[PDB]
Image (cartoon, rainbow, N blue to C red; front, top):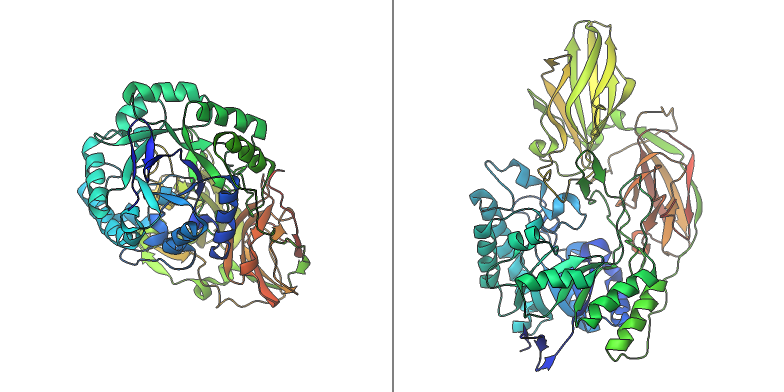
Length: 581
């Protein structure tokens, strides 16, 4: 059986090996396309593919395990094997990655007494149960069992979050028992605090970085002098938050750092080789010390392959470097996947979200506003509703706190938005009627996936108040938008500043990859044949949503667009994306 080990250098199958790995996440590309992307990586000269495992995808509700469709990690890994790649699996359980809640299921948030990523009994119990299932699926795929999985990562970048050695040791032991003799390793940033916090006794360490490999490896060598050098995440690109300029890095730049790595006899994992897409509500977020920053739908990442899988200038540039260091076959790529424009789709039908509540939700009641997790809701929008009795007059309405955006209505009139980034949590309302029906439509814009604010409840965290007076007696409608089939539509009025579903039909001669240009619109999401594309927002830099061909069918296709604020008559399908306005 093959085993990866190391002494001065990595060894596999009786020979020195340099790992040249590419990151690709199964959960970020539709399954129909996994082979295509993997074939492309192999063609570039990678010998390995590396993926995280997304716990939230696999255990969306506790005890409900999902390994189907885009979540079929077994299929993905078998695909890598077919194409001839070694596999590195990075099972977390926290994967960070710019993904909702760093891969943690929303339901962790409601576990009594839980503390994350430390030696905490409730937390470990959950990890153990999940790991028991997950490893059972992975086990046939271990190299020790003849499969392609040669290594696994123990936490992720733990040193950036904590220093709980008991936790790391427990995790190491827990993974060890569920696998074979595969190589176990950690990764961290090349800084003393990170290395001290994140290394585990007896376990190989790797570092992650975007530049300055000599420095990075030198730091690593202070803690781990003799073992082979590996950059487990070479951030050759970067990701975007809404409102940012699109991040790119030149091939020239990438090459310079790659050479630095390789010349030191370094192994490398490109992050991301293929990035793909944060479909649905799966995007992550960050928080700096002041502001919450939601990551965009596209995960193109300035990757070696584009979001839709196209080879790029970086790809050729990297292959050329690889050729200096390993002998490779003649380049042979798959036929490119066609992209088509499909033109304008008119929206002839519309439905107001506030007018559809029982069509797409079931009301729940509570004395105080609770965050959405408490109502059993992971992702999407939630409407909170209460009646105020008495004419209060002019009041300051405060949402304490708003995670992360909401639209406020009084007696069916729009009054404004509250936003997480702050000072922005207050509005002035005028309550002159005997009773006032208050409605707040809240968007979970994505759970934070890195740093100290990761305990990130969504909805309304504590309360809503007028002055200091909290409001009680709520009705709430969780809107995960999983099943829209009960919606009905008219050609009737549409109101600005109220969310509406807009429905249209796209007629397709033959399905092909395409992009929806949403530059005219303001903020929302789109569904194609029930497939949730992700979010759009006029602030950019992304202005199109990728539509994979598999989402489409010959004939009529159902396009449903939920727009939050400003409404228009149509969208247009185009053959190239706008990721960089």
